[PDB]
Image (cartoon, coloured by chain):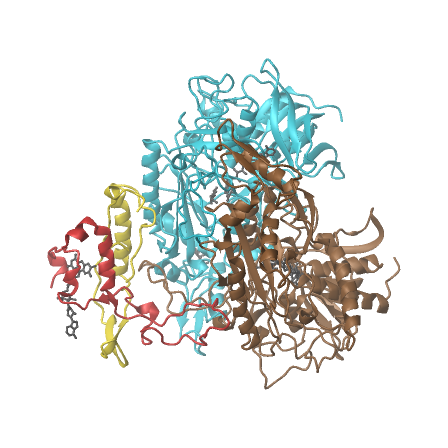
Chain colours: A cyan, B brown, C yellow, D red
């Protein structure tokens, strides 16, 4: 028996634990995955010395823990089998594929992560705020009060994640890209560091934030927190919340312990679902919310009819560029260079503090030293220079988010110092016909109803803007350099951006706003059931959604603190 | 962190943990350092495959392996990229880029060789095959007495098997496994014998195997603790060991110089005994960085004075690989005892067998699994149950077929055909040790940890190694055809040199430093030094085809006996 | 002169061709030692696109193909915008 | 200008490719390290297969090719024939 049960140990569940354990409640958290970031439970897997010295390898860690949501039946023709090999007569259901999935209306890139800390064990840590155009209303008809609410919640969420905008300021590559872009747009757009959930430890190590940063996931009481009560239970598959007959209250959480195989019925005052945009919806539908099975509009659902409808996922375009000869020459513009590298006469000098230098002394000292100590190297950028982390945030005239950076999730012969990634993310109009639904017959690897998408990017504004966004990336990137062969401008597989929203969406009125949770993240009709995550976001957004999700979670916890009393210690 | 320990161990792989298990158990005050960090979960140094999620999604573990295999020596890239835009910065030469090693001849490399820096080392991801070597593959531990040599190895290998929880029956209820085992047995009747791969693993349920690792050997918890109150052990992760300090006399190590990678500080550590178990490559790097053998490009004009055979006589196995698609005859044979009425999906469809019938070709348990699969999944056209474990078959090295074989499914792949049909074939050759096959370290180029950059000068020896390698390929082609044709996109091929990660002989064992061209004696003690020991596959001096780890652990146990008999544990 | 699942009626090729400043240093020369299949002096190039206007135009050209082509449809996967071999 | 090519236009690419002989091919430096140990294996990147050792691979027109057949390249060309405006023309 607990005051609060939380399903999922991602950053959003950790926000509930941080707020509620701290406020004195007896909290249990369950995760279907296991502890696997080291002794800091739910920490970022990139925070090893070895990954930060071999960053090209971390893409593998990411790929290792992205499990595809819905894979359609394979119809590739293999007709070069030996005559003796068993050879199929049809394209039958093989290898975990989902027969319910139309391959042409999927989000094929969609995937989930089952580990303690969830996707925050591998994420990029970009945490921008949404501007009013992207952001759901918390107050109606008072823009000032709405703005004040969001400013408060986002400030607290930034504190939890340790968001900052300064960690990359001493990168030559970063500055080279930023300064060129601000010069070229003649004031029409603002460029800044991507806000990043991270604390630099040294010139060559960043402590990336994670679920762990928000809440350390250590059982309590402990010596550091002798009056707090928290228990984490990994390898526990949460399967259903049991509704009372009034559909006014949750009475229990049904769980499956994966190690022992046993099933249990857990009681709490307050139930919080933070299992991700897909898995929150799965659990709800497995519990009798929404509609199980192929959508059937003749038999409308009695509870939460909007559940799994109005789903949004962003369009993503990507390329990489190779820095222009003009920019690389500009790195060394303050230097006086005589002679030929490698010869006794060669020298590189600058005048410290000269008012006519384009760059400050730190920069020139780095470049001078690199050039004189590494005369075999043809580039003026130091070897260990950190990566670029540049953005121009979403605006009405360029309604997409942008990242001009180096991501560990790439998608050899050219020097890495020259390479820059470009990712532009579009906003997607919520439409009732874009659906995540669950099979009534096919089950997933945890014996739960198999997720199935019925998704296409809406015609009209979403599609126009996606293409305008691709053009904008092509135009902007060209200011920095040409495309890198093998990383040409392209749309990425639908859902590979992992920004899925609106699956259990928020609004003020269940019927008028076609929604499932209120602005306290409470499920309509239910006193004691709350959902957290990107599923709550009902708007068309292009920026990275986690910070906005966390902000909604802080507001939800405030409601809980105002309405439930903790049990005495 | 104290300044003085009885024993210091460099590296927390399974061989380092063998020393820890034995010496912590005997009362020594032990410290262990690893350059990598704790990541496997609360079981320190455990197998990363041992999660529910990986065992429900085994196709994704390949990525875990790939993420922690860091290449040893990458040559300078000479690929021509002539479709850059005219505005992009464009190279005039193939300069040293992206961590490449300009000392490395691309044509004399072990390009597949890689290392793993994490607590538990490679045992956090390995395939867990642990065969014994037969006499032909194995160094002598007793001269001039073959039976005594065999007895000593059997004692050591028995103990090593216990440490690793080696077994040969974890897969005995797999239909795929027995289908393939039985077919090969029948095909080679009176010529070769087939068995289960010996596997360091404990089955927990029909769908979950607890794969062994460094953590099985020794659990890596700091001691004293509630369960080991009289033991003393400290593990120190994120500590780069850089040098063992020699006396002027080259008779003893006086300290271990370490670099704490979190604080950035450097420290000296004192021990009575020093054990280097950093892997075949990194043991050799540490020794060279400490004044043993020769730093820089080999120069016969100037042979080194200390340990002249260090880094020479290196061996790595040839590896051949393919995948097959099970024959129609074999798939049909799985359901040979079934009576089938009607057509799948119809109300009167029936698949039955007679339990106990003396005319059945399979046991009752097999037929029950088949019958239930065929009745419960009438949409599925194969008789093999969905949850059936993978095959794990071998015919071990023999003189008439001098290669090791695995007929299996490996997580380390190198999607349209049904997975139940697919079998992996890996055959591994033995490589003659030759003085000219070398691992050496740059006097100018350094690695990510500012240590002398490893460089290979390697080719498979002409003569027997090369003839055997090709005969091996042919044999995989001949044998695999008994089971099915090749899987398109996994056709028969040599894999990149070193990908098999079976490198040996870089600090090799023998009876006499000079006559046997070696670095350590049969107690794994470095010649000349009283208190320095090396463990690992670098010790193995022979041409072997089988997986080496169990052999190396056996030599470590022998080393621990010498230590326990010649050094006194401090009082608590 | 291409360089099968999408219907061919939907597919349009875009080729934009730049002008190159003549520069003395951009040369076609012939080996005094190496010969071709017809035992004639082997042709050798020493060529780069000139910095300055040729290079700036080339990149502006790429951008223009990207801008223009979008009025007609998106790129065909496997035929994305690229410089072709010199 | 055959009935067959104009009913199968996707196949003419092969006609073009069959009669475009590269002008200058640099010495190949691709690493093939998965030969069997019994196969003859190079010690250097020697001049093989018609390559031109005089050619800097980084200063080439690698796509340049010629056509030796009666009618030259006009036996396969795209037939675009624009005029030059003054700015392009001698
Ligand atoms: C993988 C990825 C993710 C992000 C980026 C890059 C990459 C490669 N970069 C990134 C992201 N977000 C941003 O705002 N900025 C960026 O730069 N990524 C997305 C981000 O990582 C997610 O939005 C965020 O974690 C979502 O947090 P959450 O709502 O807490 O959800 P998680 O998926 O992290 O955690 C859920 C949790 O629940 C568990 N689970 C699932 N089902 C069950 C059931 N039935 N019972 C119990 N527990 C369950 C999962 O195992 C998981 O840990
Ligand atoms: C990666 C892998 C490995 C093997 C198999 C499959 C694959 C994909 N399968 C396999 C193996 N071996 C077998 O006998 N059977 C099989 O089925 N694999 C190889 C096996 O995994 C190794 O042979 C064994 O671990 C070696 O054990 P070790 O001698 O204890 O060495 P490790 O590399 O495991 O651990 C070394 C250790 O030391 C650290 N380190 C390195 N340098 C330093 C320095 N300078 N200071 C401190 N610590 C250092 C490493 O970080 C590491 O943990
Ligand atoms: C191959 C191709 C060519 C062009 C286009 C498309 C492609 C795939 N499309 C195109 C072209 N030009 C345009 O203006 N519009 C377009 O749409 N292509 C180029 C065009 O095809 C050439 O510019 C034109 O033929 C050149 O005409 P030419 O000056 O008459 O030269 P050719 O290469 O056609 O013919 C030369 C000729 O001489 C022979 N030969 C070569 N060496 C010798 C020696 N030593 N002895 C004797 N004869 C020699 C050749 O065999 C050849 O026939
Ligand atoms: O100090 C060198 C110069 O650095 C440049 O970066 C500044 F803009 C100048 O004002 C001057 O301070
Ligand atoms: O494909 C996942 C994406 O997640 C987004 O949030 C990150 F910003 C991108 O860089 C990328 O990693
Ligand atoms: O390529 C590394 C190899 O190591 C060997 O030990 C394993 F037996 C192989 O199956 C393979 O995983």
Farthest residue, direction top: A246
Left or right of D50: which side holds B160?
Answer: right
Which image quadrant for residue A431?
top left
Left or right of B272: which side holds A468?
Answer: left
The N terminus of chain A appears in which quarter of the rendering? top right
The answer to whether residue B268 is above or below residue A247 is below
Query: How far from the left and from the top, in percent, is residue B504?
Result: 64, 69
Ligand 1 shown in quarter: top right
Query: How far from the left and from the top, in percent, is residue D45?
Result: 41, 74
Can residue C39 be seen here? The reply is yes
- Residue shown at the point (48%, 30%) measured from the top left: B345
The answer to whether residue B553 is above or below residue B314 is above
The C terminus of chain A appears in which quarter of the rendering? top right
**Observer-nearest of A480 and D82:** D82
The answer to whether residue B153 is above or below residue A280 is below
Query: How far from the left and from the top, in percent, is residue B510?
Result: 72, 76
Which image quadrant for residue B114?
bottom right
Can residue A444 be seen here? The reply is no
Query: How far from the left and from the top, in percent, is residue D40?
Result: 45, 75
Left or right of A275: which side holds B553?
Answer: right
Farthest residue, direction right: B571
């Amino acid at each position: 028996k607990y005051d609060v049960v939380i399903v999922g140990s991602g950053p959003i569940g950790c926000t509930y634990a941080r707020e509620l354990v701290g406020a004195g409640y007896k909290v249990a958290m369950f995760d279907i995955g296991e502890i696997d970031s080291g002794l800091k439970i739910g920490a970022h897997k990139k925070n090893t010395v070895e990954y930060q010295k071999n960053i090209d390898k971390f893409v593998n860690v990411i790929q290792g823990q992205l499990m595809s949501v819905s894979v359609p039946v394979n119809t590739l023709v293999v007709d070069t089998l030996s005559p003796t090999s068993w050879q199929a007569s049809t394209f039958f259901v093989r290898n975990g594929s989902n027969p319910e999935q139309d391959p042409l209306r999927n989000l094929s890139g969609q995937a989930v992560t089952r580990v303690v800390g969830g996707m925050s064990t591998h994420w990029t840590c970009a945490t921008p705020r949404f501007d009013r155009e992207q952001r759901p209303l918390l107050v109606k008809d008072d823009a000032d009060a709405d703005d004040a609410e969001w400013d408060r919640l986002y400030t607290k969420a930034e504190s939890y994640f340790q968001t900052g905008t300064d960690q990359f300021k001493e990168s030559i590559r970063h500055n080279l890209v930023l300064n060129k872009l601000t010069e070229e747009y003649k004031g029409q757009r603002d460029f800044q560091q991507i806000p990043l959930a991270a604390t630099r430890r040294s010139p060559t190590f960043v402590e990336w934030s994670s679920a762990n940063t928000v809440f350390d996931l250590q059982n309590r009481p402990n010596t550091d927190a002798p009056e707090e009560r928290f228990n984490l239970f990994p390898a526990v598959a949460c399967e259903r919340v049991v509704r009372n007959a009034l559909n006014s209250e949750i009475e229990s959480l049904h769980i499956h312990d994966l190690i022992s195989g046993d099933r249990f019925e857990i009681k709490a005052d307050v139930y919080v679902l933070t299992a991700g945009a897909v898995h929150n919806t799965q659990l709800l539908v497995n519990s009798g919310f929404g509609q199980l099975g192929r959508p059937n509009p003749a038999n409308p659902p009695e509870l939460l009819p909007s559940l799994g409808s109005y789903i949004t996922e962003q369009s993503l375009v990507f390329c990489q560029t190779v820095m222009s000869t003009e920019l690389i020459d500009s790195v060394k513009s303050d230097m006086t260079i005589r002679g030929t590298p490698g010869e006794l006469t060669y020298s590189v000098t600058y005048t410290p503090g000269a008012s006519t230098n384009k760059h400050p002394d730190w920069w020139n000292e780095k470049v001078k030293n690199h050039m004189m100590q590494h005369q075999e190297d043809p580039l003026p950028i130091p070897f260990e220079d950190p990566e670029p982390q540049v953005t121009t945030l979403f605006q009405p005239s360029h309604p997409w988010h942008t990242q001009i950076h180096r991501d560990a999730f790439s998608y050899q012969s050219i020097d890495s110092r020259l390479i820059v990634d470009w990712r532009f993310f579009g906003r997607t109009e919520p439409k009732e016909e874009n659906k995540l639904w669950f099979s009534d017959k096919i089950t997933d690897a945890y014996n739960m109803p198999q997720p199935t998408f019925d998704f296409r990017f809406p015609a009209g504004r979403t599609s126009k803007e996606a293409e305008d966004m691709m053009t904008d990336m092509c135009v902007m990137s060209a200011k920095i350099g040409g495309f890198l062969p093998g990383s040409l401008p392209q749309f990425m597989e639908p859902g590979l951006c992992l920004h899925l929203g609106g699956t259990h969406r928020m609004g003020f009125d269940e019927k008028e706003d076609n929604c499932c949770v209120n602005t306290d993240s409470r499920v309509f009709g239910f006193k004691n059931l709350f959902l957290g995550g990107c599923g709550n976001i009902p708007t068309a957004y292009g920026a990275n959604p986690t910070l906005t999700a966390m902000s909604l979670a802080i507001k939800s916890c405030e409601y809980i603190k105002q309405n439930f009393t903790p049990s005495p210690f």
